[PDB]
Every structure is written in C-alpha cells, then in structure tokens.
Amino acid sequence: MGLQGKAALVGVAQYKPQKYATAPRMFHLEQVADLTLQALEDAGMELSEVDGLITSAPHFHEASCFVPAMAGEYLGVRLNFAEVVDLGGASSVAMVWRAAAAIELGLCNTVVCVLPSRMAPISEHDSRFGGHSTRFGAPEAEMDLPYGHMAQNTGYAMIAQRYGAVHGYDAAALARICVDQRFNACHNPDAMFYGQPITVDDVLNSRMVADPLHVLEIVLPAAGGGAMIVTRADRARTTRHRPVSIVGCGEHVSSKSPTYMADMLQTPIGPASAKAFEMAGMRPSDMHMAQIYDCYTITVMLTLEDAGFCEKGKGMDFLRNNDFTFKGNFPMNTHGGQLSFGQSGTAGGMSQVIEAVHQIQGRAGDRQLGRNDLAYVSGTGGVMSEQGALILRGA
Amino acid sequence: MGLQGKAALVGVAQYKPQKYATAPRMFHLEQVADLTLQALEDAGMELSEVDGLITSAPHFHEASCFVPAMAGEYLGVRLNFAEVVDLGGASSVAMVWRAAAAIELGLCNTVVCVLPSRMAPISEHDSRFGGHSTRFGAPEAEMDLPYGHMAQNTGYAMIAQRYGAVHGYDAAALARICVDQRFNACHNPDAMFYGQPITVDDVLNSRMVADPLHVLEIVLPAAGGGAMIVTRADRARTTRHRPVSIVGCGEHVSSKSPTYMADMLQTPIGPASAKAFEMAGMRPSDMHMAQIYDCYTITVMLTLEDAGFCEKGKGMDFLRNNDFTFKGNFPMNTHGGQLSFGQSGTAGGMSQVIEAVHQIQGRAGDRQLGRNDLAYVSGTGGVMSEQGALILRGA
Amino acid sequence: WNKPLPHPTEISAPYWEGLKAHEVRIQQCDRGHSLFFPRTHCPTCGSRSLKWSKVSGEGTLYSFTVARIPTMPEFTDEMPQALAVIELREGVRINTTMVGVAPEALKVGMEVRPVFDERPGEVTLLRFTAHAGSHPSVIKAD
Amino acid sequence: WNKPLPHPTEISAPYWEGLKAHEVRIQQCDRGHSLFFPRTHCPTCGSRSLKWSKVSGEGTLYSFTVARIPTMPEFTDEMPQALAVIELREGVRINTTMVGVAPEALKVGMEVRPVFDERPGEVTLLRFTAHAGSHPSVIKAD
Ligand SMILES: [Zn+2]
Ligand SMILES: [Zn+2]
C-alpha cells in the first residue's frame, strides 16, 4: 500500500536566495517557465514531455484564480494533472508526493513542481499581519488580531515556552543548529550567508524577538524560487543524473493557530513522519541525512523528536551531543537550511528537497556526504500548522 | 495502473440554486461546516471519520491563503490530506478523483469535497471583466481586454461559429438540449425551472446574446453550494445508501483562452474522457447516463463528440436522432443540468455528480432511471479550458 | 484605540456581547462538548444543538511569550506585550494578554481569572490576570 | 481611450512598439517556431533564443462573433462588437476586432489585413479588415 517508488526526482533548479531590495524582478508566469526549463535541462528532458504541473495557489501575481490554466498556457504544455497547493512552507514536500501519486496512478509521465518567489515588476497602474486574515468571518481576525496575536514569531515563541516548562530549555543547545547549518552554508557558494560564520554567543547576543526566540533563530525573508522534475522510474533511467525515488510520504493538518492544538508539543510532523517511514518500510536510523524545514530553531528540534530521531523531551540533549554539519554524525540541512542558505518565501521549503536530491545524486560539491542513499525531508507551514514528510532513496 | 475502484461516493448535500437576491448569505467557513455535516448525515457517518478535505482555492471569502488549514480548523477535523483545486467549473469532478486517489493510496478513510457558493454577509469594514485578470503581466490583460474579449459568452460563441463553419450548424438541434433537459427539470421539484416546459421555438425565439448563442442556451448565475463524502469501499458497505464507486477518472488542461487551442473544435474533454474510460475498462456505449457540464449548449454537444458518444462532426445529428430525457434512449443531465436545475456558481458542476449519485443510488424520484448502474460525468471550466471526466459505477 | 478591534459576526456576537456584560460565555453542544471559537456546529461531534452559557472564566496559563519588538507599531503602548494562551476549566483555549503580572513572574500553568477591558470604548476585550493577584476585574476607559 | 488599454511589459513591449511603427512583430525561436502571446521562452521547444520577426500581418479569420450585449458599457460606441480571432500566415492566433466590414457579413476563413488603430493616442491597437476591402491600413486619432 502507499507509494511504490515508481516516481523519481530527476531535475532541479532554484534561484539563489537574495534580499528583496536587490533581487531581480520577474513575473510569476515568467518564473514558472524559467525555473521549469532550467530543471528540465538539468534532467535532460524537453518541454513536451511535461504532462503535469503543480504550483502554489495563493498570491500568484498575475492570477487570483485559474492559476494552473494560465500558467500551463504560458508555459505551453498540455497537462493531464493541473494542481495547486495551499500549505505554506509545507507546500514543497506536498507537491513532490502528489507528483509521485499522479505518476504512480498513470495519469502523468512527468510532473513539474514549481514555486515562484521573486516579486514581479511594478506598473504605474497597479503586509502588517504576516498572513493573518482580516476578512469578516475569519475567526483569527477577531480572536487573534485585537490582542496582538498574528504572523509566526510569537506563536512559535509560545510553543518554545511551553516546551521549556515541560521538558527544560537550553538556549545554547538550540544555537548549535544555527552554527552547524551556517558552517554548511559556508561551504555552499549559493548560500545567502556564504563566508559568514557565526558562534553560539552570536545567537544569544542577537536581539530578542519574543521570549525566548532571538533574531538569529529565525529566517530572514528573501526572494527566490525553484522547480523540480518528477518522472516515471523507467524514463528516469535515461535522464542525466541518479534518479531519486520517492518511497514514502505523509501529510497532516490538524490546526491553524497553535492555540487550538490538542498539545502544542505534539506537532503534526509526528503523524506525517510515521506514515512516511511506514510507507517506505524504513526507520529514522536508516536515514543518511535529514533536510528539516527550519524557519525557526524550535521547529527543527521538535521535528527531531516527533519524527523519531530522538526521544520526546531529549531534543536539547540531542542538540548538545551531535554534529549536524556535513562532516558530522547526523548531517542536517547540509545546504545551510533556510536559516543560512536563505528563505525564498514559500519556495524556501524546496531548498530542503533540492539539497536531498543534490546529496543523493552526488552533486553537493564540498558538502558531499559519504553515505548518500537515504534522506528524510520535512516541510512545515504556518505555526506547526501544515506538515509533510518524505523518504527519498537513490536508484 | 489507474484507480482500482476502492473509493465510493456515499453522501451528498446541495443548496437549492437561488437567484442572488433571495439567496441567503453565509460565511464560506459556515457553508463548509453546514454542507459537510449535511452530506455526512446523508451518508450516515460522523464528523470524527473525516480525515481528508478538498475545497476551492480562490476567492474563499475568509482566507486568501491557508484555506485548507483555516477550514479544517473551523470544521474541527484532523487531516491526512489537505487539498484545494483551482479548475473553475471542472473543480467538482477534479475533487472526486483526488479524494479516491488519496483513499486508494491509504492516506484517508473518508474525504469531504465541499464548494461554498453563497456570498458571505457584508460588513462596513470590508468585477466587470467576468474573471479575466487585469494584473500586470497577465497576457489576457493586454491581449484580451482592450479588444473586448473577456468572460465566457463571446468565447463560446466563437467556438460555436467555428463549428458551424467547419461541420455545419443546426440551431434547432442545439435547442433539443434545452428542451429535453428542461423536460427533466420539469420532473424535478428541486429544479429552478420545475413545471416550466419549453419548446424548440421558445429557444430559437429567445434573445440573441452573442451569435449564434441564445439566452436559453446559456446558464443564469445563481447561488448555492454542495458537499460530497467519499470513503473506502468497506466502510461504504455500512453507509445509508448504495455506494457509488469511482472506477475511472481523467483530467486535462491545455489552454486558458480558446484562441490558443491547437483547434477549438478538438477540446480537452476528449483526452480526459479517454483516460477515464480506459482506466475503468469501459466504453461510452456502456454508460446508462451522461451528466454533462452544461453551462453552454455548445459545451454539451462538443462533449458528446469528444467523449466518444458520437463521431466528430456528427454531434448535430446525434442531438436530432436521440431522446435525452430520462424517458429517452440516451438519458442526459437528468436533473435538468445547470441550464434548468440552476447554476450555483462554482458548485454548478457538482449538480452533475450529485445527480449521477442520486440516479445510481435510486433516489431520483419520478425521474428515476430504471437502468442506474453506470454513469459518465464531465466537468468544464472557463471557455472549454479545464476539463475532468469520471466513470461512476454502483456497488 | 488605534489597534485592531473584533468585528463580531452574528455567530460570534453572543460572545462579544457577554464580555460587555462582564461575562465569559461559550457554547456547549447537547452532547457535552464545550467549543471556542464560536461556530454554528460542534467541532468535536458535529451536533448543531449549541447552547450559550456563562462560565466562571478561570483557568490556567497554557503558554505565553513577551514581545520585545511590538507585533504592530500600534501595540507600543502595551509593550512589553505579554501574549498568553489560556485554557479555561471547560477545556477551550482563548488568545489574550496578561495584565497586572510582571513579565518575569509569568509561568506556564498559573491560575488566572478574567479581566474585562473597556478601554476600546464600545467594544469590551477579554484579558486575564493572576488569580491570586489584586488586579481588578475591569479596566475602565481612560 | 476610456476603455481598458494594454499595459505592455518588458516582454511584450516590442510587439506594442511594433504596432506604433505600423509593424506586426512575432517572436520566433532559432528552431523556427513562432509564438504569440509574447514570452521569454519558446512554448514549443523551450528555447530561450527568440527573435522578433516582421510578418506581413496577413492571415485568415479563424472565428468571430457579434456582441449584441456590450461586453462592458465602455464598448458601447463600438456596437455591434465584431470580436474576432485571426490566424496569421505564420500560425499564431491574435484576438482583435474587425473594422471596415459589416459584422454580420464576416466569414470564417476569409483573408484579412492588419489595421493599426491609433485612436487611443499613445497606444496603437491592432485591428483587421477584409484583404480585398477598401479600408485603409491605419485609423488616425480623431
Ligand atoms: Zn459535540
Ligand atoms: Zn522553439
């Protein structure tokens, strides 16, 4: 049951994360074409082979609706699967397994998952709340906003405060995530913070946003984008690189605000990762790498626990006693993660997937892992809201 | 390797189509809850069983993004599949096969497919192009709008005019679609035009909207909404009515504007229907009913041709030589279709799926088909843009 | 008051009206499930039989944080923002802020009691304080 | 013009500038595929090496319709709107309207000529007319 591993990632492409002030301006339709063709060239396939497309539903600059039709028309493809997702940072992992499902279902042969994240040029004839809805009837508009609750920082901070009171807290242990991932980024010329190492005290000395989260434990919004090609296992054999099979997946959404979680310390990556490991017939100890969605340090540590890599409540202990660099025993976000490689909006989650593909394909350069067969990848949207997991295995 | 038919429609719910003046206003989250619970009650299931949710992505009144999360939180369900679609009128059939794909893949036991279509209450603190985008970079904003091309009426008129030039045109033949479907609605107390029979003359003498399309050949806009429960085959055994298995599906999007179609007369419902018939191991001649998306009479005739019910260029004569009432030899849109039952905005296409479920479950009252086991269902968005096809089979 | 205010719907209206009467009123389905935020259905069992009833309003601090950068510039006069999540004895959770408690004494699990904030004017907001503290139950408009 | 006007992008600017020069410019990849609307890639083969080719603007009327109800009030002075789709000799299709011919006279497949509509002032639009007709190739602003 579940995915049988007959779909594989064969081509990737992504813009270098760059600050909004200086990043190139590109229409979202233009980005869709540019990123798809780049990823197709990386795979060694041409345009007419694409019979499936997945992208993000909200905030597509040129279309408030009919996004698949307009994007596919601009691209020039004939789609048997016209898909959009609306899961925030979890979107990237959500598109990957949907592409595999459609290919294993026989609907498609080759699916492109693409997320534009650069802003479009401005015309003379043409966000405070951080994504919270102000619409009449939206519960959070009347229950969150009047009290200052909004966006993501303070929500994740209240999760961190709950964890500290229940299981203990070590500010320096969480800072280990920033230091090791920055080390990884310091060996990635494409990373935003390439050549910019940090220390533990650097993180603690950075400004407090909301107790106990510091600015350096939080991603810096940036522009970018990315796309990935998924195709059938047989066609994958004649592509350019090692196929990266999609052998397990999981998805879970049980709340929007963390306030209505059954337990803010039981995050949805638990159920999602248990389904993905089960589907792949594998266990956390089988993985050679973990590309973990890292908008906040606390999200990484909670993913470490709930995905089964360490015991619930010993996350700080796991962070103190392990080396998370590409030279370490538990390589993690070996591209730098969104924290240090840069967060390209909703495409930031795709950096995790692409790095897993790079590592498995033997294309990671100075950061290449010795064991590069098996990868766990997570995606997280909102504040512990939307979650997905992937198990990937090289051919 | 398509669907194995292990998911089934078990419960439906549908607001009666109403003009926007009589139409009550409810929040889209409110409609999600109300319609979901009505459909669950129709199937005899509980809210606790729902672990999958599909709805429409754009113009969700209370949320421009994170629609699955806000709706799932408001409804109170824990989702292993959080899905949105952006395919216009083809959204309903698109949701059904996605729900079956997730159930057969093992992620969900029960998926709710819901489309709010009533407007929300207005507030002090809170569209002349008919859905066309005006955004900078949208191709139709500069290639369509300044020349008056927009909305749907003229686009379908230009497809009809092209057909008449290539294959000949018979306006009285199209009128039979209106007459026979109105006859069906005349035996449907829930239909908008219940008890109001019309003749071919009434259709031909109605006002011309855009040559060669008459007023009576075009749906009128109305408010409504619908929900649909899909569940595993085994759980469907103990639900209240006959399970309606989803044995075949297909999807195709190859153009937004018909101007860029390879050929406006070769429409994307063909490829989608061929895949659905192939996957169900079935032929058009095996169907006991055809519930065809009918926002325009020309859509129905082209769907009959391209789906395989008659030869290309012969659709005019098929309309002349067959009886499309529920008493006829080719029962079609037996609830009256959107033309005579009412078009509930985006939820209009759901009326085609619901009527098939009603027929297959033996719940269609006076219009009940004696032979009620196999159904072909189509959904169409835009101007022959987004297309989906379903083959449904009673248990 | 330049901050965001609630714009009650006809679904949530009885809750914001109860606060105006210095009462915390939440819905309870006919099977015994309390719910919040307000809905037209029970998010636990789906029942449509909901009854509004006053609750004592006391509970525990489920979690909290202290904003050192204001979440919005118009919350500067509330700084530092003691953002809090309260779980009433009924088991529902309410977003709010703490008043009359030093940020450094905030502690996950403290007993809390409601404070009705009339400063916005026509709208009454719901804040919380330490149960054993002396902070009054109402904050009148300036 | 009070009606909607094109807002050219850096991608489509050469086409709209071409109309100002009384030219119909259509992109072609170096593999020979023509494309419209304008893009930065070939929608056929994915090539990024595109050139702007000068075409005669001649073609055939692919389809048409006569608007009896205005697509919006702003086009009432153009009634009845002869909405049209032209297929150029090179194979691309263009949305437009027909001028210099009766709307009810049109026929699918008839040969057409381009007509550069300068009436909006700074923006020139592309209309079409019968190839054998007497309508000029330009409409000078009023
Ligand atoms: Zn209940
Ligand atoms: Zn080309």
Image (spheres, coloured by chain):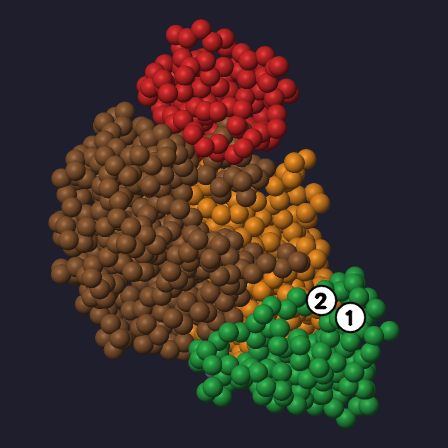
Chain colours: A orange, B brown, C green, D red
Q: Residue at x 43, y 43 (%)?
A: A69
The residue carrying pointer 1 sits among few (fewer than 14), some (14 to 19) or many (20 or more) residues within 10 Å by Cα, namely some
Which quadrant holds the C terminus of chain C?
A: bottom right
Residue projecting furthest to the bottom? C132
Image location of residue B181, percent across then percent down: 25, 48
Image location of residue B238, percent across then percent down: 25, 78
Label 1 near ligand 1 (CB < 8 Å): no
For mark 1, name the chain: C
> Along the line of sight, which residue is nearer the eye, B58 or C63?
B58
* Visible residue check, residue B100: yes
> Along the line of sight, which residue is nearer the eye, B294 or A44?
B294
Disc 1 marks a residue whose amino acid type is Pro
- Disc 2 marks which residue? C5
- Judged from the image, the secondary structure of the residue bearing numbered disc 1 is loop
Q: CA distance from mark 2 to mark 1?
A: 8 Å
Position of residue A320 relative to residue B202, above or below, is: below
**Mark 2 or 1 closer to N-term?**
2
Q: Residue at x 26, y 48 (%)?
A: B197
Q: Which mark is residue C120?
A: 1
Position of residue A8 relative to residue D101, above or below, is: below
For mark 2, name the chain: C
Image location of residue A164, percent across then percent down: 66, 81
Image location of residue A223, percent across then percent down: 63, 48
- Judged from the image, the secondary structure of the residue bearing numbered disc 2 is loop
Q: Residue at x 14, y 43 (%)?
A: B322
Residue projecting furthest to the right? C142
Whether pointer 2 and pointer 1 mark residues with C-beta atoms closer than 8 Å, the reply is yes
Position of residue A276 relative to residue D64, above or below, is: below
